[PDB]
Amino acid sequence: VFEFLFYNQQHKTRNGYFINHDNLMLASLEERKKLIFYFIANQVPEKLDPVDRVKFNEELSDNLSTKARLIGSLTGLIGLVGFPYISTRIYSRPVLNIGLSLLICPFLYYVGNQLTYSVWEPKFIANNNTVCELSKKYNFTVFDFAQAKKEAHLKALRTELVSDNLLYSPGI
Amino acid sequence: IKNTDLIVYLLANKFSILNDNIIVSKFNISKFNDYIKYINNTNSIDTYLENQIILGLNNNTNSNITKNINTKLLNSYSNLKNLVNITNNTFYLKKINDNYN
Amino acid sequence: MIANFENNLLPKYDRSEVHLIPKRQWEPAFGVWENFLYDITEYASFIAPRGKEIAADYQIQSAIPLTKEELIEAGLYKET
Amino acid sequence: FTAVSWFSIYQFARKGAVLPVLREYGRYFGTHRLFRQYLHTLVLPLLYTEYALN
Amino acid sequence: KFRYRLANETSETFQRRNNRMVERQIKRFQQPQYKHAFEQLQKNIAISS
Amino acid sequence: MFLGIFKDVIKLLNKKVVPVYFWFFLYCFLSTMDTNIFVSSCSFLKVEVFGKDENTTLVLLFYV
Amino acid sequence: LGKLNFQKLKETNPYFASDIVNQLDAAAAEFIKVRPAAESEAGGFLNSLGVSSSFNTTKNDIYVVQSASGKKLNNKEQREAYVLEKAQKYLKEDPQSKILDIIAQK
Amino acid sequence: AIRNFVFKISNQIQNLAAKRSLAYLNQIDSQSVPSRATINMKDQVTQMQREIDNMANVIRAQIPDEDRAEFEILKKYYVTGQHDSLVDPQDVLLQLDRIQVLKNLKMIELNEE
Ligand SMILES: CCCCCCCCCCCCCCCCCC(=O)OC[C@H](COP(=O)([O-])OCC(O)COP(=O)([O-])OC[C@@H](COC(=O)CCCCCCCCCCCCCCCCC)OC(=O)CCCCCCCCCCCCCCCCC)OC(=O)CCCCCCCCCCCCCCCCC
Ligand SMILES: CCCCCCCCCCCCCCCCCC(=O)OC[C@H](COP(=O)([O-])OCC(O)COP(=O)([O-])OC[C@@H](COC(=O)CCCCCCCCCCCCCCCCC)OC(=O)CCCCCCCCCCCCCCCCC)OC(=O)CCCCCCCCCCCCCCCCC
Ligand SMILES: CCCCCCCCCCCCCCCCCC(=O)OC[C@H](COP(=O)([O-])OCC(O)COP(=O)([O-])OC[C@@H](COC(=O)CCCCCCCCCCCCCCCCC)OC(=O)CCCCCCCCCCCCCCCCC)OC(=O)CCCCCCCCCCCCCCCCC
Ligand SMILES: CCCCCCCCCCCCCCCCCC(=O)OC[C@H](COP(=O)([O-])OCC(O)COP(=O)([O-])OC[C@@H](COC(=O)CCCCCCCCCCCCCCCCC)OC(=O)CCCCCCCCCCCCCCCCC)OC(=O)CCCCCCCCCCCCCCCCC
Ligand SMILES: CCCCCCCCCCCCCCCCCC(=O)OC[C@H](COP(=O)(O)OCCN)OC(=O)CCCCCCCCCCCCCCCCC
Ligand SMILES: CCCCCCCCCCCCCCCCCC(=O)OC[C@H](COP(=O)(O)OCCN)OC(=O)CCCCCCCCCCCCCCCCC
Ligand SMILES: CCCCCCCCCCCCCCCC(=O)OC[C@H](COP(=O)(O)O)OC(=O)CCCCCCCCCCCCCCC
Ligand code: HEM
């Protein structure tokens, strides 16, 4: 009955969007650099050169993003199992079945994607040779991390604002 | 088991209860809902009148060992007729004089 | 009303009593663990159910009334 | 500890008392309970000492 | 009042009333229904425990 | 009894108790998108199906 | 004809089969009640790629039988006599019947 | 000694359990507290069942006669067939769909009369 229904919430528990100074404070030097690089690459790729952007995107798709999408799709198919859920030789209730499927499948996809991220994101950050090498190369600082955090929040705000008028928007 | 023999056995068992339409309720007392329904639906008056029978916990071996009554103790207390009077399985204490000095 | 309910056909004497349950004497030929397992299985198979039955019988006999014939034989009741 | 335990076991066996520990006879060689008690009293404390020191 | 009957009645009157009550209770128990109730109560002692 | 235990393990892993769908899901979960044989070779699944952050048109067509 | 009648009666009243089964099993034996439950023969994902849990559950139930009309029901001895008489008649009709063993089992 | 102490503990525990499980049958406890507790439990159970029944009755009285049959079907199912395996919900769904067929026929008649 509040923002958690109509606002955007799929970007807050994924892609290291939750990384802040608390993790960096306890992290060692190398761990801090790796975390900062991961956050910057996921949220504000603009700070990276095109080659690094492409390489990091390929690694992310291979490890976390596409894997979570596939797992969510498998869970959604599991939900689809048994369709139509309620029907008989007289009526099939197509609208009710469509509503039930649309309500159930995306929830299972979300559960699967969240599971995949929770399981693999820490391992990907900790034990990825590509991420380690790129973090060593770039050597980001706490100031860079703070700038990236502000820029990521502003990007989320811009994305929310742009989709304000999805039906009618003359402009002037 | 032969199909015909099983069918005959089932029919005989069903008709043994009564040669008329009957109503059967199945309850699993281990479950809360089933137990509450079973206790609500079972009435002692019907069981006594034989309009209802419960099957599943027969436990027909209810014949006790005929607990012996303490005849010796009862006779010992009867012999004390100056203190206790026995009537209708009731022990009445004869009133005593608290002022005995 | 049930609080003040009373049953006058029950025996009026105390029903407390002693029951004998024979034991399994320790067997030195087995050993500590074998004897312990024997004792455990005996407790689970004979001693425990026997005591449970004794306690249930004690609980139920305190409610089971005495028959009229038994009352007459004991002299507790005189007919008419 | 081993000497005290052996002395106690010997004296109580001489008087006819044997602690009811271990089987009376062995499963394979039929070694007596007294012999196995002596063996255990000799070996177990050494193993415990080694483990504690390690 | 029923619980503390004895406090208000004399020995003889209490004995008379209690004897009448006990005789009537004995007759009621000897009535067939009470015997069936007691038999049913004793029937399932093992399961109820 | 070792052969009996092996037979019991095979039976417990049998299809009727441990679904092949569960096995496939476990394989996908344990393997990455470049090692998974079912999708590493296929560019369409790895890019067009699962590679797009928003594939509403294809999802709607598949659902229909 | 039997199958069509069963289908029509079940559709008219879903409790028809349940009532008949309860009536049959009321006085049935413990080994009769021990029988398993029906298995789903339908195919699809749950049969090919998934696993469908069986319908079997605990079978410790108490059958409370009450006469709709209200007539007195037969006691245990009367029921035993009725079953024995029916078994004797069936054996006379067919010597090879094992109704005696079935009854003696429980 | 140790065995006797263990058996004494076991006997006390068994007596306590037997009391706690079957004290409502006898009048050993003055005022029959366990008996009154059991009677109260049975009264609460019966009152809950009769409360469900009376709620069903009042809803039935207030329900329109057009869907009174559907309410009857749903009530009977929720009471009996929910916990029964032999009762196939497909037949109940078929009855509901027949009622819905009648309702749709009436609706279309009203729309296109
Ligand atoms: C314990 C477990 C349970 C509880 C927990 C559950 C948790 C999970 C929940 C989610 C998942 C499970 C869901 C289960 C329930 C599913 C639903 C259900 O119950 O189904 C049975 C049942 C469905 O009915 P049924 O008896 O089974 O019948 C089946 C149908 O026949 C089947 O349909 P059909 O096949 O008959 O087809 C019908 C079709 C007919 O098919 C056709 O032939 C189509 C005919 C129409 C064609 C044309 C279509 C386009 C028309 C356009 C018209 C103009 C539009 C204008 C729009 C303007 C917009 C501004 O009709 C249409 O679709 C056409 C109508 C379109 C809709 C209405 C349009 C409104 C327009 C605007 C109106 C106002 C304008 C005002 C203007 C100014 C004044 C004039 O449910 C109900 O009856 C009610 C259910 C209510 C559910 C409420 C749920 C609330 C949320 C709960 C969850 C969240 C909160 C937490 C709760 C926790 C517990 C307390
Ligand atoms: C502070 C720490 C945090 C936790 C809180 C604190 C917890 C404190 C717990 C204290 C527990 C005290 C228990 C006292 C028992 C006193 C028994 C007695 O009366 O003594 C006389 C008794 C005299 O024996 P007997 O009855 O005359 O029989 C001799 C006959 O000649 C021979 O008669 P037979 O041949 O006719 O038939 C018997 C024969 C028949 O053959 C058998 O049945 C032998 C079976 C051998 C084991 C088979 C499985 C192998 C796989 C490994 C174990 C996995 C667990 C599954 C075990 C399944 C059941 C065995 O078996 C025997 O010989 C019986 C004795 C077997 C002793 C050898 C095994 C010892 C270790 C057992 C496992 C302990 C847990 C390990 C967990 C994992 C650690 C990484 O003394 C003995 O001979 C045995 C004394 C054992 C004392 C154990 C003290 C343990 C203290 C440390 C506890 C913690 C351990 C590490 C885990 C830590 C977790 C945090
Ligand atoms: C590192 C070495 C340290 C050595 C220290 C010195 C002491 C031990 C060695 C002494 C050797 C010479 C002794 C004098 C011999 C005189 C002649 C004679 O008649 O013998 C006296 C007497 C036997 O005569 P008996 O009249 O036939 O008495 C039979 C009674 O049942 C016996 O009744 P009981 O009164 O003796 O009581 C049963 C026995 C308890 O005996 C049991 O039955 C307990 C069994 C526990 C099994 C736990 C799970 C094992 C899982 C597999 C492990 C694989 C190896 C891992 C190695 C890791 C790296 C070290 O003792 C107790 O329950 C009380 C003590 C509490 C347990 C403490 C045990 C500590 C043992 C430490 C040494 C282990 C060496 C392992 C060598 C490799 C084995 C593969 O010998 C002993 O008392 C010594 C027993 C030594 C342990 C035997 C274990 C047998 C079961 C092995 C199972 C796994 C392999 C199965 C292979 C199957 C075929 C392929
Ligand atoms: C915990 C261990 C995790 C290990 C992970 C390891 C990685 C591999 C995982 C493998 C399993 C998943 C992939 C294969 C699935 C195959 C399914 C299949 O074909 O079976 C046919 C199977 C046939 O059913 P059935 O066996 O006949 O049973 C009939 C029951 O009605 C059907 O239900 P049921 O009683 O059989 O139990 C399933 C039941 C739930 O059961 C559980 O909880 C499952 C518990 C965990 C089971 C784990 C099994 C796999 C273990 C693998 C690892 C083994 C390791 C061994 C090695 C050693 C380890 C030390 O699921 C549902 O039906 C849930 C639907 C409702 C949504 C609930 C969630 C959202 C909350 C909604 C609340 C609404 C309240 C009202 C409104 C409130 C408003 C405020 O179909 C289904 O059960 C369909 C389920 C559809 C929904 C599934 C997705 C929703 C969430 C499910 C529960 C949460 C777990 C999600 C997965 C977590 C993964 C980490
Ligand atoms: C007190 C509890 C409830 C509290 C919340 C109440 C919310 C009321 C508003 C409608 C809610 C519909 C169900 C929940 C949807 C949750 C997601 C959501 O609302 O997404 C946003 C979107 C509308 O947002 P919009 O303003 O158009 O987009 C601006 C973007 N910057 O959402 C939509 O466009 C979705 C709704 C479209 C209109 C549908 C009208 C008919 C109802 C259909 C419901 C879905 C089908 C369900 C069928 C099975 C269950 C019955
Ligand atoms: C939809 C209901 C139709 C009911 C028809 C019958 C009644 C007629 C009487 C007048 C009714 C006027 C109703 C106006 C509702 C406006 C709703 C609205 O504002 O919705 C949002 C929409 C665009 O917003 P969106 O891009 O989706 O996202 C949110 C933006 N922050 O906002 C806009 O589009 C901007 C505001 C537009 C207001 C227009 C009002 C006059 C419309 C006249 C249309 C006449 C022809 C319609 C067809 C024939 C009707 C008989
Ligand atoms: C013509 C057929 C072509 C395709 C054939 C093979 C398809 C097999 C896989 C199914 C599709 C999976 C798509 C996954 C990527 C994706 O969706 O990508 C688009 C987004 C990605 O989500 P994120 O942005 O959070 O990563 O998906 C979602 O938002 C969730 C939608 C559901 C996805 C899983 C499928 C559920 C079942 C679909 C039917 C139910 C209704 C769906 C809405 C109308
Ligand atoms: C194990 C399962 C599958 C394997 C191994 C597989 C493998 C492949 C491979 C190797 C290609 C060639 C990619 C390329 O051109 O480089 C391909 C293309 C394609 N596959 Fe699959 N595939 C599988 C399942 C599916 C399914 C289920 C669909 C559709 C429902 C599908 C649709 C396609 C399409 C449309 C193309 C063409 C893409 C293009 O031309 O760009 N495949 N597949």
Image (cartoon, rainbow, N blue to C red):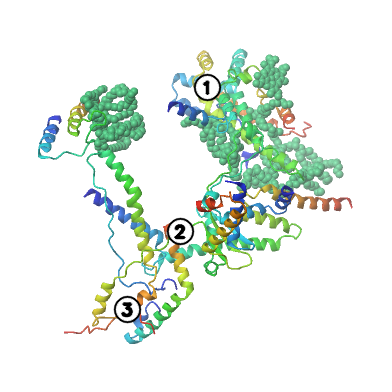
Say which element carries label 2.
loop
Chain ID of residue with mark 1: A
Q: Which mark is residue E19?
A: none
Q: Are marks 1 and 3 in contact (CB under 8 Å)?
A: no
Question: Residue G14 appears at what percent x and percent y?
Answer: 68, 52
Q: Quadrant of residue D23?
A: top left
Q: In the rendered image, which residue does mark 2 sit on?
A: B59
Number of other residues with Cα within 10 Å of mark 1, as a class: few under 14, some 14 to 19, many 20 or more: some
Question: Residue D6 appears at what percent x and percent y?
Answer: 13, 32
Examine the rendered structure and indicate whether residue B21 appears above or below residue A133. Answer: below
- Looking at the rendered structure, the kind of residue marked 3 is Gly
Please give the name of the residue rendered at 73% of the width and 34% of the height, measured from the top-left corner: A165
Q: Report whether residue C37 is seen.
A: yes
Say which element carries label 3.
loop
Q: Report whether residue F54 is seen.
A: no
Q: Are marks 3 and 2 on the same chain?
A: no
Please give the name of the residue rendered at 67% of the width and 34% of the height, measured from the top-left corner: G44
Nearer to us of marks 1 and 2 is 2
Q: In the rendered image, which residue does mark 1 sit on?
A: A124
- Quadrant of the image where one finds ligand 8: top right
Q: H37 or A36: nearer the eye?
A: H37
- On screen, residue D3 versus residue C9, left or right, reads left
Examine the rendered structure and indicate whether residue A38 appears above or below residue G26. Answer: above
Number of other residues with Cα within 10 Å of mark 2, as a class: few under 14, some 14 to 19, many 20 or more: few
- Does mark 3 have its CB less than 8 Å from ligand 2? no
- On screen, residue C53 versus residue G52, left or right, reads left
Q: Quadrant of residue C10?
A: bottom left
Say which element carries label 1.
helix
Q: Are marks 1 and 2 in contact (CB under 8 Å)?
A: no
Q: Which mark is residue C75?
A: 3
